[PDB]
Amino acid sequence: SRQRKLEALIRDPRSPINVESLLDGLNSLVLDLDFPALRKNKNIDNFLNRYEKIVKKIRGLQMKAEDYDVVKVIGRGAFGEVQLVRHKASQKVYAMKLLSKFEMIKRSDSAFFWEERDIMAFANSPWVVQLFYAFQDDRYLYMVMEYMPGGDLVNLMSNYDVPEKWAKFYTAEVVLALDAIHSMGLIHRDVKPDNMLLDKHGHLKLADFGTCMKMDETGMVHCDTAVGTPDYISPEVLKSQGGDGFYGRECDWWSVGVFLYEMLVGDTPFYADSLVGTYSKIMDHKNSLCFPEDAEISKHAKNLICAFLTDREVRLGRNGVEEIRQHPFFKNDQWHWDNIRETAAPVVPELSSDIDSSNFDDIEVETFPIPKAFVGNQLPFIGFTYYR
């Protein structure tokens, strides 16, 4: 019998108790105890007298924000920003996402990133944006990701009248990407053009994974919270808010339908002035869906959309991705499914240099209160740090 299994767990970079997680655990403990009020406790003061000095030192050898140059800001979420950065020593360009620890604690939403980190770190797929380094300081999480200089599809669709030839391509790439995520045992749950980014050669990678979830042995989730963003959410996910909902990956294919509809027609199928408007339409989709007379659309395209926008029970892709691939809409002369991502994309970005952010739009003070007793504001972020 053996400490052989023990050693194994510590070296595995997927493990929750690898060396970097353990150092996060020691660092976070020191950050949460080192306040005048708490040091009135002998145990706490004595502990910190031993480790405070060495923990400062460790933190100095650690990757920091100051190791990067901020070239410019290219996106702002609810929890922080996305920066185009150049790492100083290597001189290489990355996209760095910052998540404010303050805003995540405050909004009670401080565990969404574990799946996103895992997927980007280890997917090793051309369809998934790659994470190179994850690190933290007392105020932020940082994810250093490969930069996608073609911008998102929400930007492509707003600069072009998209013909069907193009939609075949982009839809197919979304289909393969999602199938990749599903084969890693995960349902995306937030498929939309904002999370679809175009690489240098004009091909697509999925970029955000903050709503992902692991499936059961069977292929399902049990989830009682509706998630994703209103316009693209499926009826079964929305229904599951009320309690004991029980869905599989077919919820993502709904979102493909919404995406394909938007790309050809120019507006989302269930668009409405209000949130509760859009939700009321999605629920009543059998009656609310219809294409305007004038926006002219192929009968195969229209069919594919309707094959996606139906009840889970008969939705295209309930039997697996195979029936999606053979749908007549995808027939064309440029690409088959094994080679699509090495053919010429419909829009190749024009870039001047390795810091060209021209496909992103331009963009234009908050601390934890000092504690009394022990709040543990850093505990949710132990295990985040990762080096490639």
Image: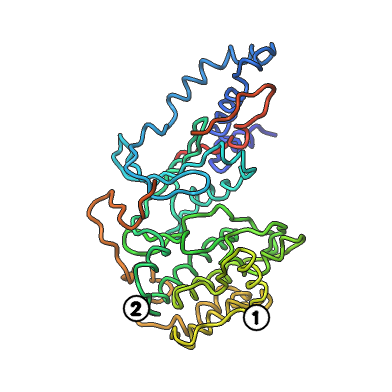
Q: Is residue 329 left or right of residue 48?
A: left
For disc 1, the marked residue is 286
Q: Tell me what residue is drawn at x 39 percent, y 82 percent.
A: 332
Q: Is residue 324 above or below residue 189?
A: below
Quarter of the image with the C terminus is top left
Where on the picture, by quarter, is residue 228? bottom right
The structure's colour scheme is: rainbow
As drawn, the residue found furthest toward the front would be 273
For the residue carrying disc 1, how many other residues have a C-alpha within 10 Å: few (<14), some (14-19), or many (20+)? few
Q: Tell me what residue is drawn at x 69 percent, y 57 percent.
A: 225
The kind of residue on which mark 1 rests is: Lys
Q: Position of residue 38 (x, y in %)?
A: 66, 17
For disc 2, the marked residue is 334
Q: Tell me what residue is drawn at x 34 percent, y 67 percent.
A: 159
* Between discs 1 and 2, the one toward the N terminus: 1
Cβ atoms under marks 1 and 2 closer than 8 Å: no
